[PDB]
Image (cartoon, coloured by chain):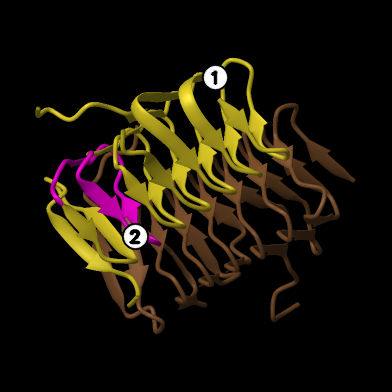
Chain colours: A brown, B yellow
Amino acid sequence: SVKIAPGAVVCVESEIRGDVTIGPRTVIHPKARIIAEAGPIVIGEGNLIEEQALIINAYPDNIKPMIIGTNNVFEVGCYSQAMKMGDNNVIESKAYVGRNVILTSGCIIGACCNLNTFEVIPENTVIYGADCLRRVQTERPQP
Amino acid sequence: VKIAPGAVVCVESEIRGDVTIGPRTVIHPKARIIAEAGPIVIGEGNLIEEQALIINAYPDNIPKPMIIGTNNVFEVGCYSQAMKMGDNNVIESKAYVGRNVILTSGCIIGACCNLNTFEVIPENTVIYGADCLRRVQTERP
């Protein structure tokens, strides 16, 4: 069953299936898909999931919960299987974040980037290029 | 203050003056939207987070409207005077964006940055760096 915090804004035209928990201040646009397939999904306070974004707790390519922190922006048509994500991240339009990727905090995944890697992204990283071959440090604080 | 059907304006928010709010836009508690020197027009699907400040102010010099597009994000505590913004821009927590800064689409202003220049930021630009002087384009317009 789907559990939304009072004061979260989830549009009727979004697709939300499985054991999903939505923190307060979170907003989910129409046509966003959130699917707790292989395990629960937990979304924290103050995230934005935009149109056609796809978030899925999927079975891997081999034989539990997906945890998302606070203040992350999932831009239109992006696709995430990352099982853990911290705070203050932005995933840009049509970027893909793979199941073996762990996002920390303050990161930016560039538009159209296909990040299907096995790694923990250091804090404050920007990864961009369709290829995902470029990385810089934001050097910004967090608060 | 004109609010479109399907927009969500939280009760503890502050909206003053000639402000138009498009459908699906969400305005959180303690956000401030002030149309002081001119109107503010805000499009669809924007998100204005707690304690964000958006103001159409008189310039620091001696009524033109502020125009904001679709799916832009004003994170907690940020402060914007930009008079024109397109689509899919993210202004990160506690950043400042100036009156003569024009954002196109797909931009990200790094947390706590102070961006008070005279220019049109190219699409898909990330403002970052220790002094917020570094820029990169994640993708071409």
Residue B59 falls inside the magenta stretch: no
Residue B13 is tagged as 1
Q: Chain of mark 2?
A: B
Residue B111 falls inside the magenta stretch: yes
The answer to whether residue B50 is visible is: no
Say which quarter of the image contains residue B11.
top right
> Is A81 above or below relative to A68?
below
Residue B104 is tagged as 2
Mark 2: few, some, or many residues within 10 Å (few <14, many ≥20)?
A: many
Query: Please, what is the three-letter code of the amino acid marked with disc 1?
Result: Ser
Measured from the top left, where is residue B90 in percent x and y?
Answer: 41, 49
Residue visible at 57% across and 54% down in the picture: A84
Q: In the rendered structure, which segment of residues is drawn in magenta?
A: B99-118
Measured from the top left, where is residue A38 in percent x and y?
Answer: 80, 64
Element type where label 2 sits in the image: loop
Alpha carbon distance from label 1 to label 2:
27 Å
Q: In the image as oriented, which residue stretches furthest toward the top? A: B12
Residue visible at 77% across and 55% down in the picture: A14
Say which quarter of the image contains residue B113.
top left
Measured from the top left, where is residue B74 in percent x and y?
Answer: 43, 39
Query: Please, what is the three-letter code of the amino acid marked with disc 2?
Result: Thr
> Is A110 above or below relative to B140?
above
Element type where label 1 sits in the image: loop
Quarter of the image where the C terminus of chain A is located? top left
| Nearest the eye: B126 or B80 | B80
| Nearest the eye: A50 or B35 | B35
Magenta-colored segment: predominant secondary structure = loop
Q: In the image as oriented, which residue stretches furthest toward the right? A: A1
Classify residue A64 as left or right of residue B41.
right
Decide which of tag 1 and tag 2 comes sooner along the chain. 1
